[PDB]
Image (cartoon, coloured by chain):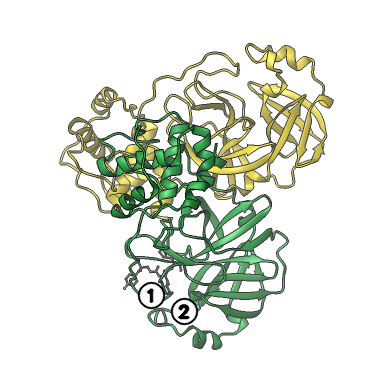
Chain colours: A yellow, B green
């Protein structure tokens, strides 16, 4: 198994650059609106505790330089929605895909199109950690790069990049501008919650192992969801939700292994360790493949 | 540190579907030519010992169905170049990027756009193994998916997918239709030569781990180039050349760790192991990042 990103072309066709003064970051051009992080209006002096509302009142449409490549897009309105700026432009993007804005849950994966100056540089798969950070590869100038999933013709945008935390992990918002996690767009001291292991994804991984014939860890027992959750927390695993149980449905049906029976197998692995054994050729349990990722690869 | 693929849009706009009889795979549509694996012209009974020139002379332009989305492209000509079929169509692709065809060297990396029925499905980074296989993720119908690198505006196509081996690794050709490795496009179980580990890439990745503040594997020892290479060969690592040392200069400068010092750290890891420890998340030494890959992402 490997991290596989979605093809990025439908998102590449939406990337632009947005500049205020000397600050350039990326924006997302859909129909006649460009979405970008509101901290584009900050000077270095405003970043420690910006008054975004006061900073925005000082701005006019003609202060925003929006470019697709070297071609300027004229701004005809502006507004702030939580931590994102929305710039109305006079041209509808002809490459606008079918799209929606979604707010994902921890554990869910998405593709990131890393961009600098409106130009895409790379694409890679990210997992939203339970502490609402991602382990991106984001340099200066990457803000406004987005994360997405593609289903049929439809791009679901779920992430827009805003900042790096002291530990090197990354934080951002959904496309309505609401941060994931307890972070704020100020250049202040912020730390992530201690991270935990994404249980639903480990279970997906165990299902993948079973599909591929590697099933030594299956046992004759079961558990309740509550009993499993109380044990899992003692090993720094996330508790399962009802939604987690539901999204394991398809893999449970494909293997005939009830979700709670797999939980009992995982509980035994946590309590007894691997005893020098491997699963899918690894003594480490993987937690960045979702149930959908596993189906995406195993079955095509 | 993240494996990062090139943005795939310039290649997505070239993918089409090619069908012959009951066989469907992907093709690459550049200007007015579609490139695809020639085994699309095979049936079940053909796959075992296909005399491709014989099978092809018995085909007409009209036996080839090419679809770009919902639109059928009329084939007005065909030819074979090694293991690739070239179908001339009456329409030019306006989305054809600036491109070239290159043959890559073992140890080099590229992005794969995996496709099914002419539709892009996923993108990921691969390395050409020293034994000329690739560790891909390819399923039924993935043939004709391509691998590529992008430099500025220019797409360098280096790989077209043809087959899976019994071990689960993959084999294919350059865009001139010559296989990488000793493989043949017949429906037989084929083994590769013994694989080895790409040493210059492991060193690049260790330098990456250091840059990201991870240096538990470092040491004060050093080694000569020849003595390192003796140990490498013993562990089925590829030789490290002076060109490789030179190529690693920038990473050496940035971290202030001489290449041969990092060679001494790798030698220790080979002889002793990781003793449970991990490097950049991995229990294993990673060898599919090139020096250029590490830099580009730093
Ligand atoms: C694309 O047409 C397809 C891609 C394969 C399918 C699954 N994963 C892939 O990468 N190519 C082939 O199926 C290829 C066609 C030949 C004409 C070159 N053959 C192939 O990949 O065979 C797979 C294999 C596992 C080797 O199956 C076996 C065939 C014969 C045997 F004796 C034993 C196994």
- Tag 2 residue: B42
Secondary structure of the residue carrying tag 1 is loop
- Tag 1 residue: B187
Q: Are marks 1 and 2 in contact (CB under 8 Å)?
A: yes
In this picture, residue A263 sits left or right of residue B238: left
Q: Is mark 1 within 8 Å of ligand 1?
A: yes
Q: Residue at x 35, y 56 (%)?
A: B196
Q: Is residue B145 above or below residue B59?
A: above
Ligand 1 shows up in which quadrant of the image? bottom left
State the CA–CA distance, disc 1 to disc 2.
10 Å
Q: Is mark 2 within 8 Å of ligand 1?
A: yes
Where residue B105 is drawn, which disc sits there? Answer: none
- First in residue order: circle 1 vs circle 2: 2
Closer to the camera in the image, A25 or A51: A25
Q: Residue at x 33, y 51 (%)?
A: B232
Secondary structure of the residue carrying tag 2 is loop
**Quadrant occupied by the C terminus of chain B:** top right
In this picture, residue A108 sits left or right of residue A218: right
**Image quadrant where residue A76 sits:** top right
Q: Give the percent coordinates (x, y) of residue A96.
A: 69, 44
């Amino acid at each position: 198994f490997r991290k596989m990103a979605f093809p990025s072309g439908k998102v590449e066709g939406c990337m632009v650059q947005v500049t205020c003064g000397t600050t350039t970051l990326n924006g997302l051009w859909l129909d006649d609106v460009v979405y970008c992080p509101r901290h584009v209006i900050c000077t270095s002096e405003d970043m420690l505790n910006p008054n975004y509302e006061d900073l925005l009142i000082r701005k006019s449409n003609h202060n925003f330089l929006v470019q697709a490549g070297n071609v300027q897009l004229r701004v005809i309105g502006h507004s702030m929605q939580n931590c994102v700026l929305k710039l109305k432009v006079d041209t509808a993007n002809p490459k606008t895909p079918k799209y929606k804005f979604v707010r994902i849950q921890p554990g869910q994966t998405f593709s990131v199109l890393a961009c600098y100056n409106g130009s895409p540089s790379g694409v890679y798969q990210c997992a939203m950690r339970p502490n609402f950070t991602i382990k991106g590869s984001f340099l200066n100038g990457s803000c406004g790069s987005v994360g997405f999933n593609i289903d049929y013709d439809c791009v679901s945008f779920c992430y827009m990049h805003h900042m790096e935390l002291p530990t090197g992990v990354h934080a951002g918002t959904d496309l309505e501008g609401n941060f994931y996690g307890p972070f704020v767009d100020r250049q202040t001291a912020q730390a992530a919650g201690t991270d935990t292991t994404i249980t639903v994804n480990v279970l997906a991984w165990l299902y993948a192992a079973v599909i591929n014939g590697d099933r030594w860890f299956l046992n004759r027992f079961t558990t309740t969801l509550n009993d499993f959750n109380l044990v899992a927390m003692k090993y720094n695993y996330e508790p399962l939700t009802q939604d987690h149980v539901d999204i394991l449905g398809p893999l449970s049906a494909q293997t005939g292994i009830a979700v709670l029976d797999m939980c009992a197998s995982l509980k035994e692995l946590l309590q007894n360790g691997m005893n020098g054994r491997t699963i899918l050729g690894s003594a480490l349990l993987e937690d960045e493949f979702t149930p959908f990722d596993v189906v995406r690869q195993c079955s095509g």
